Image (cartoon, coloured by chain):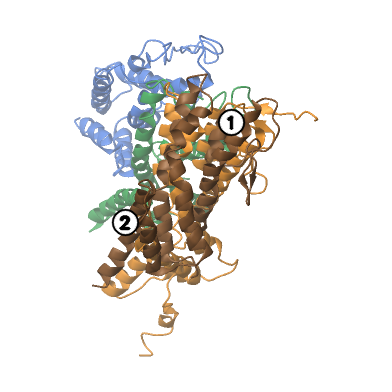
Chain colours: A orange, B blue, C green, D brown
């Protein structure tokens, strides 16, 4: 046997790191990035566990990081923290609805960090992944919903179809959980809230049309494409 | 802590004084440059903001303090009523400062006086007084403040230019004093 | 780290949070205390605070500072004054939400910037949405009542926080034009 | 080696506790740091642990052929009734941290409540997986194995019975 060269780490440091990665942050010392895939960090070790067992519990959390590093990698873009007269009013009701859920879990990951600096009581990986189990269970729902609904879209498309596919995908996603018993009444009342915000610009556009007659489909947002009115209300 | 006497010093004693002296050195403030019991540059950049509000209160009050008594030979009687209303304003300012609990953080002070500190920097630079020697200027931009018709019309022009603004009722109060003569 | 940051987000930079006029608030990228986990959380906060430094500058530079003396319309006016008071009234929420941390960074003896980043992540949403408004003004040389169109345009952005902030700016500037119309008619 | 016994009676594969998809968990080495009698106890612990591993693989495979709504309902049932396993293996930390002297033989006084349950209930998804079963026919094999002797197993598959009957009660609540 040739000696490995390895770095000892206190497991609460690993726990600080995941609470950062999962609060949607960047470039932890553990959970290093290689190519937009989050990775373990290689020769990083403790005592009560070996090297490759730790590696395998990091892999599972890094693949959960990806979901929310990628949702954060999309909450950064379409809201602009990183064209003129191209405001997609649908991807600024979606990608706002991706956010006021996030608080009530970026937060749980504070009140967790809190007992982890500000008290005595015993906490460890087996006491905390089971603590988070009723919430990482949501993020893998949320990744199939956004993977299918938006990360599958091809590079060039018009401001009708890119909204239409998302407006359709949330509806079939809630029907998949509405019928399957009371097995997690979280996930139906997770998924219904995302759709109701995402329909705001369509349900607004229809209100102007229905009550004030004129419709303002600017940046060509809307299915019925009133490019006809450009030559008409006189060709009668 | 080492500071926060700035509250009464918006009127005057040391941590925001004018001290009508040499601008380079003897123009003095409680400025512990380097070391000084451990507070960093950041707090100096807060304290040297209330130096601006402060030296404009000390200098605008210094400007408004001396009476004229119909005796200064350069100051027609409108200027007396003008300076009287200006002292009414400075008395209201003291009445506000001194009501303030000292049990507030430095940031609360640095934000709470944004209204008055902004609107008093106006009255100072409206007059000749606001650009004398707050620390940036070195006794340069003093010029002729008007008196008589030239005062009371220019006052009306300021009331137009600010007919809607946060500064407006002050200008109306000063103009309604200065109409008296 | 502690309490120095709250002086940095309020507009009083120094020592660790080095202000630079190009990038804004910037942290110094190599320390013995701070591990790789956490300077990149300060940069998120520093971009919000940079937009607040960059907001206080644009407020103070267009009321009280000058009285007509060339007082060019495209860089002043009865409107741009009153926008920056609307903007002052829109920044009261940020000032309040930055005093409410002062009673913890030395009123609750430990915090980590993860709680700060969360607590101010509410304002991480509002500021770039009004930062684009003042960057539209500074590049398009907007003027007079032709700012009420810019305000009312981005008041049609569907995001309810943003649609309240630029509504409260809109009430001030309608105030002004109402005054002018009470004047004329 | 007492925390790796505990993470590999939980899921995750390691290095003491070798895994293979056929054999299951399979400590097999000739350790100089244990009394030689030890490894056959671990292969017995690995048994239930693998009736969590392979018994968990089925769960993540779901939630068409086999991917039916009543199989999801049974399988998210096999989450509700499986959570007592997960929890009963957080609680197995709190002794061994404290008492320095407890040997792994304690763990078998503890978990052998489950040794009546896991390899019996393992035949119901192995049956559903080795045959194929669809629709409300899932809501039969559940009941035909519920008619057992063993009172542990006879109330594992009576909780999964009522949570998947939750689906039948609703589909037959639209319909009426």
* Residue furthest to the right: A2
| Labels 1 and 2 touching (C-beta < 8 A) | no
Let me know if residue A82 appears in the view.
no
| Secondary structure beneath label 2 | helix
x, y (%) of residue D166? 31, 60
In the picture of the structure, the residue carrying the numbered disc 2 is D162
Q: Residue at x 60, y 31 (%)?
A: A49
Tell me: residue A118, above or below residue C74.
Answer: above
Chain containing the residue with disc 1? C
Relative side of A154 to B66, left or right: right
Tell me: residue B177, above or below residue A95.
Answer: above
* Residue furthest to the front: D149
* C-alpha distance separating marks 1 and 2: 58 Å
Relative side of D103 to B13, left or right: right
For the N terminus of chain D, the image quarter is: top right
Foreground residue, B104 or D69?
A: D69
Foreground residue, A34 or B66?
A: A34
Q: Residue at x 26, y 51 (%)?
A: C179
| Secondary structure beneath label 1 | loop
């Amino acid at each position: 046997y040739v000696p490995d060269d390895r770095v000892l780490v206190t497991e609460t440091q690993v726990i600080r790191e995941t609470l950062w990665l999962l609060s949607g942050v960047k470039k932890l010392f553990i959970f290093q990035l290689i190519d937009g895939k989050v990775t373990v960090r290689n020769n990083i070790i403790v005592t009560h566990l070996t090297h490759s067992c730790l590696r395998s519990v990091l892999e599972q959390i890094a693949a959960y990081g990806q979901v929310v590093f990628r949702l954060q990698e999309f909450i950064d873009e379409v809201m602009g923290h990183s064209s003129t007269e191209a405001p997609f009013r649908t991807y600024q009701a979606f990608m706002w609805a991706l956010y006021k859920y996030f608080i009530s879990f970026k937060e749980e990951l504070a009140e967790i960090e809190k007992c982890i600096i500000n008290n005595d009581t015993t906490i460890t990986l087996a006491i905390v992944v089971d603590k988070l189990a009723p919430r990482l269970s949501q993020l893998k729902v949320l990744h199939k919903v956004f993977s299918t609904g938006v990360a599958e879209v091809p590079p060039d498309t018009r401001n009708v179809v890119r909204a239409s596919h998302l407006l359709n995908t949330l509806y079939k996603a809630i029907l998949e959980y509405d019928n399957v018993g009371e097995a997690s009444e979280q996930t139906v009342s997770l998924l219904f809230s995302l759709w109701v915000e995402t329909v705001r610009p369509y349900l607004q556009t229809v209100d102007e049309w229905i009550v004030h007659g004129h419709l303002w489909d600017g940046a060509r947002e809307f299915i019925i494409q009133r490019n006809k009115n450009v030559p008409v209300n006189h060709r009668d | 802590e080492l500071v926060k006497d700035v509250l009464n010093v918006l009127i005057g004693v040391v941590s925001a004084t004018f001290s009508l002296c040499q601008p380079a050195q003897a123009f003095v403030v409680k400025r512990g440059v380097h070391v000084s019991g451990a507070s960093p540059e950041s707090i100096s950049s807060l304290l040297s903001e209330v130096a601006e509000y402060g030296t404009c209160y000390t200098r605008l009050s210094h400007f408004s303090l001396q009476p004229v008594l119909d005796s200064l030979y350069s100051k027609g009687l409108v200027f007396q009523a003008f300076t009287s209303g200006l002292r009414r304003y400075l008395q209201y300012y003291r009445a506000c400062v001194l009501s303030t609990p000292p049990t507030l953080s430095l940031l609360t002070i640095g934000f709470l006086f944004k209204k008055l500190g902004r609107q008093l920097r106006y009255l100072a630079e409206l007059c000749g007084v606001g650009a004398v020697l707050p620390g940036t200027c070195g006794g340069g931009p003093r010029a002729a403040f008007p008196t008589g018709v030239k005062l009371l019309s220019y006052l009306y022009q300021e009331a137009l230019h600010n007919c809607s603004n946060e500064h407006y009722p002050v200008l109306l109060s000063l103009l309604k004093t200065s109409c008296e003569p | 780290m502690i309490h120095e940051l709250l002086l940095a987000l309020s507009g009083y930079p120094g020592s660790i949070f080095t202000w630079n006029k190009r990038s804004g608030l910037q942290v110094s990228q190599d320390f013995p205390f701070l591990h790789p986990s956490e300077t990149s959380v300060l940069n998120r906060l520093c971009r919000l605070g940079t937009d607040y430094i960059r907001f206080t500058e644009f407020i103070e530079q267009y009321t009280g500072h000058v009285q007509q003396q060339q007082g060019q319309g495209g860089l002043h006016g009865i409107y741009l004054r009153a926008f920056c008071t609307g903007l002052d009234s829109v920044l009261q929420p940020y000032r309040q939400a930055l005093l409410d941390l002062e009673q913890e960074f030395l009123g609750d003896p430990h915090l980590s910037i993860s709680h700060v980043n969360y607590f101010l992540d509410q304002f991480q949403l509002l500021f770039p949405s009004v930062m684009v408004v003042v960057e539209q003004i500074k590049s398009q040389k907007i003027h007079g009542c032709q700012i009420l169109e810019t305000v009312y345009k981005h008041s049609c952005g569907g995001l309810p926080p943003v649609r309240s902030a630029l509504e409260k700016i809109l009430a001030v500037c309608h105030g002004v034009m109402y005054k002018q119309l009470s004047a004329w008619m």
